[PDB]
Image 1 (cartoon, rainbow, N blue to C red):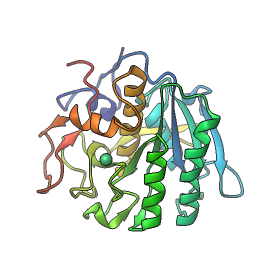
Image 2: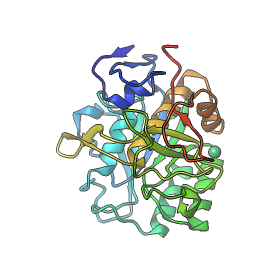
Image 3: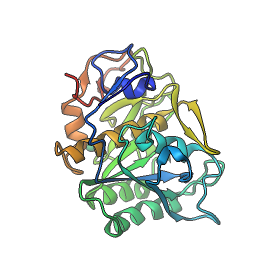
Image 4: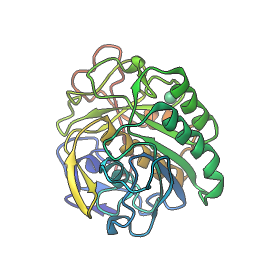
Length: 279
Ligand SMILES: [Ca+2]
């Protein structure tokens, strides 16, 4: 399948090269997989989700995304225009209030929630979780990411936005999950991407068009926007049969565009997520 005049990041993760605007992907498109967006919530009523999205948890007084962040990230995963994995089932978990703030202990509670709940859902092709959030190093926050991953969920986490080595941030520094940095449409590291040997992979994160609340769209920027490209990609690769929840971060790295970003500091991977469909 081909989707012309696509947001640049969907074209990128289907290209070897920058500078084009079609998104090339196999039509199975994540059918039979499940992606949990653990964030401010998802405006499931957005027609771009077409009935595939459900809130299933909150730790606040409403499950609605009253911020926009969770809806943007979820759209990149799996909205019909703006998503990677256009036939995946989306499940929301609201661990952030309507300003973007979550206490750690609640974020932990969300995370163990997914390791349990996946067992209430129909996900024959595999389960992913997408965490576009974080704060300073915590062993506990990190332990809750290793548990979620260990429970057979592909876990994808934002490296962080301080232009700093990510080993000081959580859940990014955790080893066993898939820590995602960001890039721009000219294959530069985005100016705000944390870096450091704990990163596994980079994704489009600067000027990412996606869904927003009210039924609407916007372009925003962050390792948060990069993260759901890799989550959606992993859902897409499960569904096909290329990899598994426990093998997908390795698998994406093995198949990435290798050398191609500017400004990988020394010691940071220079790997860019790629679906290997067109070549
Ligand atoms: Ca890893």
